[PDB]
Image 1 (cartoon, each protein chain N blue to C red):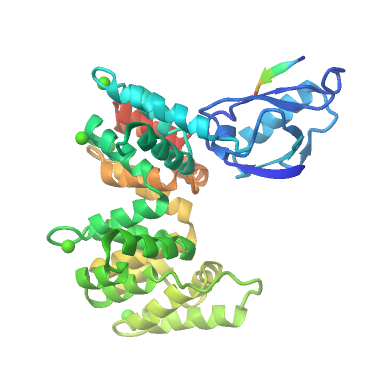
Image 2 (image 1 turned 135 degrees about the vertical axis):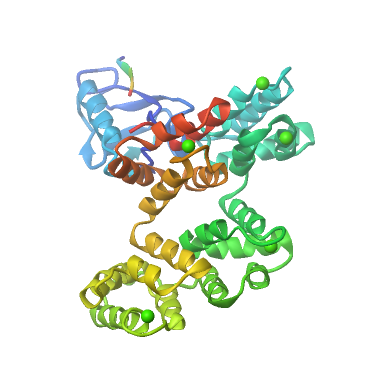
Length: 6
Length: 405
Ligand SMILES: [Ca+2]
Ligand SMILES: [Ca+2]
Ligand SMILES: [Ca+2]
Ligand SMILES: [Ca+2]
Ligand SMILES: [Ca+2]
């Protein structure tokens, strides 16, 4: 659900 | 399923988005959602969306919060002191497929055929693909146009940018072999370039250069060196170019470390004149870690260190070659950092040197070069390249640098 561009 | 992937941290961005964490019931495990072109992960060609992240630089990513994984990977990627980065992943095809190569080739063809030529796109793609990916792109380009990519880009580009891009298209051994051929072309010799390559390449690199040079030019590299050089400088270059240095051993030979240090002193500073063959044999045959220790032990016998001893004992091309060789043995990233600084520090730019180092070391040890450069000169390699170069040529070099420090 959580998507984060590192 | 479990796999350890090493990735350089030289690129400014890792170039991935992640998903999941134990605060999530839909995805308890953190996985890769997307890989972006332009980042480290894409360059590895070993990471695909869907891979289950397990560990990064020894820290654990299994059964952690989404924020824990984000911050842990970020902290690892920003820690440039540990190169490369180790990414332990769990699999459920190549990461860079035939379709990816065809897409890159299609976009380069578009850029070449655009009115005025779209150099930004050409640079954006090629300086952000690995050397292996560039070979795939050239293959796909020829299949779709029936023309060679290098020839099309030679016609579409000019100036220093052309030099960068055509250099990037060659394999490392092709690039070095072609630069060695160029150093020996015309009347006289570009000794600085011959010395840089021959003194810095490893046995494995030189094995492939020797093979590829013969294939490209139908003569052995050693024969062209013999034709173009003379004296003890020739003897040293021929010896180094064989790529037959002793391999690094698992046992440190302290007795030989001391005997070599004493022999270097007896051959040079201790006596009138110099026994140059003794210097050549010790500095070409012994392993690099052994010689690092020899040069430290040499300072116990000699009032001058090895580099200062060379300046006192020999001159001309021979002196230049020994100074370069000893730097390469002592600290090769610092050797290249210093050559980069020298190529930019004064009026204008020694673009030939700047380009060759950025092309040839981009995928070898650029982060260590950058670290040594920033420590010594106080500002980053990126900063110096920005002040000394401009335009799309500058942007290409900055992408090969990877990021600022
Ligand atoms: Ca243009
Ligand atoms: Ca041209
Ligand atoms: Ca010549
Ligand atoms: Ca002497
Ligand atoms: Ca300058």
